[PDB]
Image 1 (spheres, chains in turn brown, red):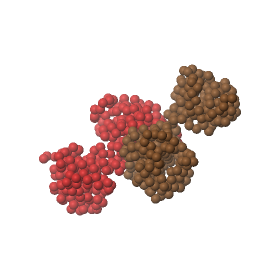
Image 2 (tube, helix red, strand yellow):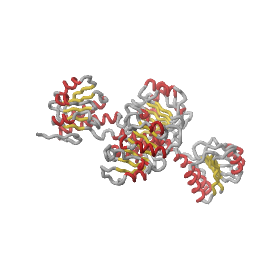
Image 3 (tube, chains in turn cyan, red):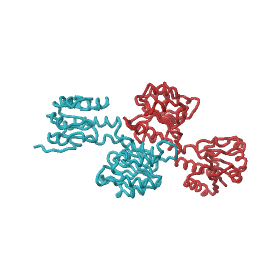
Image 4 (cartoon, one colour):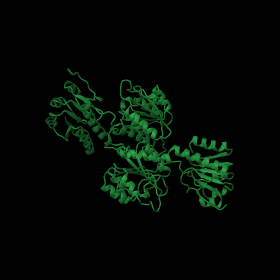
Length: 302
Length: 301
């Protein structure tokens, strides 16, 4: 099997080495396409390919049709918007991503941000400590679970809410977390259910010095609601890796508000090698055993 | 026993409550002197005092002489130069601080700064993770041991150096820590030996993407050495709660250098209440049982 690796933004050298090792041992061929400047470059190369690994590169219909006998394309990372899924279905091409490969990067950023917020951005003033505080974890997926492990490590007590997962001690109503926890960590997927869900009435319930850290999406916040409660509750802190739309937070709440300029939760060298190497092992597995765990598309075999 | 509590900057209300509880339960009386102005306020009130708890307040000879039957003063905190130790010796007054009460504050600041450093100050760019990296702890006293616990909790591998205390696995020479660890944390006292010890030759040995986090003293760094090596090694990161003297770090090394505007390691509400109640507890213990653990002075009886 020939495996082409298409990356305008190349993986780090040790990641490439690892992808090589996983596939050459099994033992397939690996062919790199790195820093290509022209759509045709990838088209020439992909014609003989059985498999593909990509990062955020656009894999469109033409490219996919050039890939006559490509059976599988693995996105090293979370999103796959960059790949034409319908054109892949048309061609009986299994499409995967690599879920859970950024979890520690996002969780450590959450913990760092919590310490940062509790310490006034490492500026002058009276700080607080995470040890012995109760953390309310919202979403107990990949990220949520790792945050629990780190938060416990540093000596926080834990409560959890997640309406999609069943886990040992979860609280039933999210209101309960906000009542009973000093610090809230948000790791929920954005849906109609969760859209705008974190708003005035809920946030209001936090105890004095309450803190909310958001590593997920801006849209699960009710921005005007959070603004209202922060204006009346000057003790509340909000730290987020997903900047709000409203410019009010930055204008009014300095000293108890921080947003990264860009979502950096997953921007770690480790996240990138974890994803690249997961992509390799998942492709090895597909050809070895037909394993299609993490397949994000589906098609008929008529 | 009458115990007076002298604080221009008062304790938080719950700290006061806990200090009250500890002393009134053992049968003593607590007199609070908060927000006071002048010095008369303290002198008049200290006359009848058997003991004193203070923070950064200046306690000079005049005040100490006013307290004729004062037997013990406890500084809720680390330092105690605010107290005239000579006058307390002359007076046969036991003086204590409360060591180890700010340890978690400094340790959490250290880990926070490490994540911060590794994630470009929470700005755009390629970050790294502490999990699975090897941390070299320099100094394994109160702060050092707590940093060990937190760093372990979040998945770092640990190696330690401390020429003062003997611990299970310590390395013999600092050079070994700097060769074998990705991240170094500094919690060493400033000493003839430690002064300017962290310098060019030592730092240069760090692996690629090396990071040093200092929460102790600025003086254990050889600033010119650190400057020279950071200019050569653009990969190296330096984060500190004790800002350097030289302007160069801020001018040249943005993106791989941060210093807090002042030392905030111990500035947490918890550190303050830990210290206030340790002081109360150390006074109860002194009167109840004559315990003089943490006494920082000595005198002829």
